[PDB]
Amino acid sequence: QVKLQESGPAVIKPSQSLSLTCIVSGFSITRTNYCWHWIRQAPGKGLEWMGRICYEGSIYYSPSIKSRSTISRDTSLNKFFIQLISVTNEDTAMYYCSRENHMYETYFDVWGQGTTVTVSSAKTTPPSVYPLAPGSAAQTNSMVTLGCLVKGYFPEPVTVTWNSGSLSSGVHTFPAVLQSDLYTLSSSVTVPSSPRPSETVTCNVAHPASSTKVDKKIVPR
Amino acid sequence: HIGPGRAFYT
Amino acid sequence: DIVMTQSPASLVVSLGQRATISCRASESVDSYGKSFMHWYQQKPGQPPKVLIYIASNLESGVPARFSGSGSRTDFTLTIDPVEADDAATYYCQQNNEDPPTFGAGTKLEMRRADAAPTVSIFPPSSEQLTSGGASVVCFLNNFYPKDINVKWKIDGSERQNGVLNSWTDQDSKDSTYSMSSTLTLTKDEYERHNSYTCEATHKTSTSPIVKSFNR
Image (tube, rainbow over all chains, first blue to last red; front, side, top):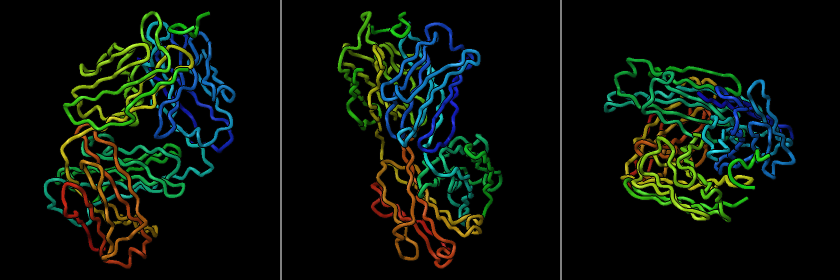
């Protein structure tokens, strides 16, 4: 039924134009009453409203963005956009588009996933995936933890799954942390000690800003 | 002018 | 325009209990005799989810235990009994006049019985060593509460620095936390020392949980 997908650049040099695109899908920009909004949330902060463009073209901007912003749509493609001129680090945030029934309801009922945007002069560098296999220890109760080390990539984010989504339980995936403009991340899966080594366990990491996708099977040591 | 519809009042 | 003031900024409530978040608006958010302010919930790395709209009305799916109250300038979300899943930030928003505005968020973290950490230590993968680098990794999984201290003792010596720490957010099924430490060494550095160890010290056991290996 409705889908919204934000797309934009992972990274952008300071003092350049951020331009995002929100792609409504399976519902039209112009059905009456809906207004289409942009909301951004700077990391570890609150949602902040940026502006809306209502189904029939009325636009409205948060003062703060007003004079460095331009919200336009494209009625034929069924997508809308926003341009943020002369970005700085305070533009680094997660950007969301959502939908509002402005006549009967007043609230944001559909929201896209949100892309992330990092304003930085750094280079997007792809990730090294290293398997974490228990250094030499079987008969370790009935469970084994194994993990993946995803070291040195930039900008955020990374997806990492285990056995392509099939291992859903036991997984932990820890926030990326910085090592002077480079990220390291890690994920673990605990599994009963019979499917590892016997069955295959693989972490799958994808780091879309560089279109790196690597699978890594955790073999014993 | 407040409330619903506010936006496309016109 | 209206400034939306949520309070408390954060709070810890135990399972089965009641939490009361409140959101105050600098001016009335009312028109057509309805209060046009809504509450949202945002589990981490999830878009906000509507919970309650137009001050009292519950959105489909949101369980019984969410109660939207108040009017004009005074509004109260009440979750009782709190459970697992509600470990999240809650925002209230007005959308009665331009620009619409959000509260600052209230983080609900919530209380369970103190669990102790399953720690796991993993040596370098050969791949990294090949590339001249060596990261030793210790997973201190599934505990409550979050305050936990890790000590990286290589050959008797706490290697003070060269270490990285990340903690999950609270789990939305068992309410725990988990964290990972990455001690990162030069190949050779690692290549000149037979033991490495992480010592988790934490409320549940007075005795630091030690785990180690031969280089």
